[PDB]
Image (tube, rainbow, N blue to C red):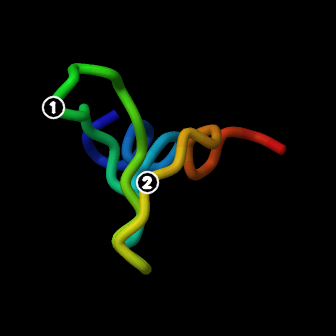
Amino acid sequence: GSPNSSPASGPLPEGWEQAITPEGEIYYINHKNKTTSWLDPRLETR
């Protein structure tokens, strides 16, 4: 969905980038206050 279909249904807004910890566990990074959280992705779907 290059044009948008994909980076629009599961994008990563500035302040929420997905990555992996040195341990290898997958988690989300909050650059807003430099903190680590395991809460569902940005959009998720509350």
Q: Where is residue 34 drawn, in percent x and y? A: 35, 72
Q: Nearer the viewer, residue 36 or 5?
A: 36
Name of the residue lying farthest toward the front: 23
Q: Where is residue 22 drawn, in percent x and y? A: 15, 31
Q: SS of the residue at dot 1?
A: loop
Q: SS of the residue at dot 2?
A: strand
Tell me if residue 40 comes above or below residue 16 in the rendering: above
Count the numbered circles shown: 2
Asked if residue 17 lies left or right of residue 46, the reply is left
User: Which residue is at 21% across, 23% downward?
Assistant: 23
Asked if residue 42 lies left or right of residue 19, the reply is right
In the rendered image, which quarter contains the C terminus? top right
Kind of residue indicated by mark 1: Pro
Q: Nearer the viewer, residue 40 or 6?
A: 40
Q: Where is residue 16 drawn, in percent x and y? A: 41, 60
Residue at numbered disc 1:
22
Distance from the alpha carbon under mark 2 to that under mark 1? 13 Å
Q: Is residue 14 visible?
A: no
Q: Is residue 8 visible?
A: yes
Name of the residue lying farthest toward the top: 24
User: Which residue is at 44% across, 39% downward?
Assistant: 5
Q: Label 1: few (<14), some or many (≥20) within 10 Å?
A: few
Q: Nearer the viewer, residue 11 or 18?
A: 18
Residue at numbered disc 2:
36
Name of the residue lying farthest toward the right: 46
Q: Tell me the quarter of the picture where residue 28 sits.
A: top left
Kind of residue indicated by mark 2: Thr
Q: Label 2: few (<14), some or many (≥20) within 10 Å?
A: few
Q: Earlier in the sequence, mark 2 or mark 1?
A: 1
